[PDB]
Length: 313
Image (cartoon, rainbow, N blue to C red; front, side, top):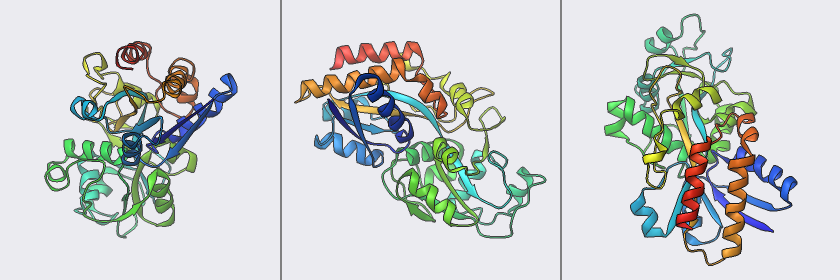
């Protein structure tokens, strides 16, 4: 029995692993196309897939208009990644305001006084910062630009947030893989990817300062610390963005991937089979999530989701 899904590259490393493990355990096949959140929303609204995947949650008004249900799948994090010589992953430090100024093109050199001051003892080149951003409609760009809007008033007014924004500069890469590839190809570059892409490529991601003023390294622990303040119980359709999370251990660009399905499917058998996969992922696929440095959904959230499936589908 075969289900089809498409969307967010943010969750693709996890969906791929779950699909292989779910097949071993049940004999069922899950097919997933990594095409970005914009692509995911478009394909599910076109009815070409059984599920769409996006890291930008849709609001209740949009879900009602489209006849869709929405639920989280797993929590991850967006991380700034760099191509700098002699920098270990996590070593480079940026505040949210400084990261905003870099992506705005206000801070254009690696030896800019703010970068040097935040990184004592780090050797920085006297070269241009080469920006890399997503070219496609992206949930990773949504969570990144959403975070930047909260910590940079100039970013909020000039660029704002969304699956696509008007980037002041840089090159555009397709998908998280395309941003990773461009960062590897260009010396002195800076991009943003979901943590699993920095880890599989052995790329230097940066530390970021959280709203509590602590220097944080992106990992399942810091993502979980950010997720700990999420009020999922009071969210409608799980519409909640968890960037700039409070508290001492939170990674400031923590994000949730969401799955989208039709509340009244034309194929009841395939829709039931889709929910069969997601129930397995949330109940039996937590080790796989932790292994890839995602945060598996906690039990109360899984209960809320299963109740949502019951009432909406």
